[PDB]
Picture 1 (cartoon, rainbow over the protein chains, first blue to last red):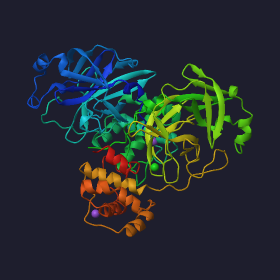
Picture 2 (picture 1 turned 90 degrees about the vertical axis):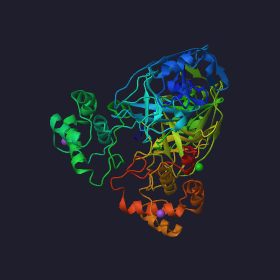
Picture 3 (picture 1 turned 180 degrees about the horizontal axis):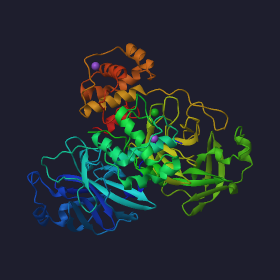
Length: 301
Length: 301
Ligand SMILES: [Cl-]
Ligand code: NA
Ligand code: NA
């Protein structure tokens, strides 16, 4: 019935985005209940950027140093604290649009939607994956620090990501909403780059199952490999190794298609060792790895 | 700096989505002010599939035949009319979440966001384009009819598409919000299929300009072409011809980068004969045609 990279509807998050200014720096904050969450580096001036002491930088800050704007309304900051790399600003008014939400930390290879904002205003929404090297291959420009990534489960918004910085290659790095970085990154203007990335193998298989449910099936073969034998091949092509937990996760698509996982791995192993022979799968010259099994489950039933 | 495919934030449209039921058929409606818009084929039965006489069928319908549900609230229908292929149900309650909006009819090559919905509930958002053959390559499962396409470039939601039906190849056809189909399609189950699709050349060129802005250089060359020689090559690959209007529109991008339009056309001619050869343009081994010159200029600046 058609297949596309889909983001979650962003309305529940749009009602939470506000503008946070400290000094001359302006970025995005997330207004939930009576706290605004944003990257702590909003308190840095030009001199601190090299190696900032965030402990002493925030002691010196006062509540009135933070301008928080929700549209025309200025929210009064009545407290401030720091949780790892995230700044928490207590305001005097709970957000009446606060959705049902929780903070979650995701694993590499999991997907979520980003609501890209600038100066507090939602600009766009896109679906992405946490790469195995803990970067995000989205692109929002400079002013998008504090934009957030999220999933929606039933009616609950799960916030999993906050944008802090762009890396030299144009990929982005950030934290969960408790301020813990994804990846070996620090929120200082120092020498940082993304490690070598790998392909999220479990998502490629999920997407191969999607191509099979779409009737695109030229790649299916009669053969079956072993998990050990497949990982030796995949690890040589900078593919993430495939675990017994990954196999079980794919189970539903296995029983639905009649393609056992290690049967489908024999297909993927030849695509690795042969290339796609000038063909496409689901209209791609390359193998898509930002569809999880659950993304493939939902978008077909 | 990798230009990703972003949708518009969908919250303003989410607040307009309702569920419309006639008999056993449920689909989505668009609730703006005191009117709900939906595909008129909602009034068809299983006998009415091939050759429904919509004016005969609508006359026989009473306001009480229409069940409209906004969440846990039923909206009473107090009138109904037809405008082309779009049913308009007057309701006794104006939608308090009605945004600033307009209805526009778009041209092939134009992009927009789709809020894919099921039983009146928003499910996902994605970005797409009106194909030259007047179809959409989307993801519409059973009951996705009445989902809408929109842009929100400034403050105003411009509604440009309502989904009516899926064609044999799985692409989608629909109308503008005044009920006029895009392309030669009709809301009957008589045999119909999409014509051969072509690539939106002006959008490919905009995307190459965005790659250069992003710092790609590898596909540039020292050649130019004439507009006529380029169109002879382009059509041999089922690319759309480039008009002088297209050359004018690319003018801004030509001047930001210092690369003449017909200079860039020579690069595209070369990419068609050689392929990517392993390389990627803005993280893609396919030439992307669903990013317009306007989209590029926006997500730059
Ligand atoms: Cl247009
Ligand atoms: Na096989
Ligand atoms: Na050239």
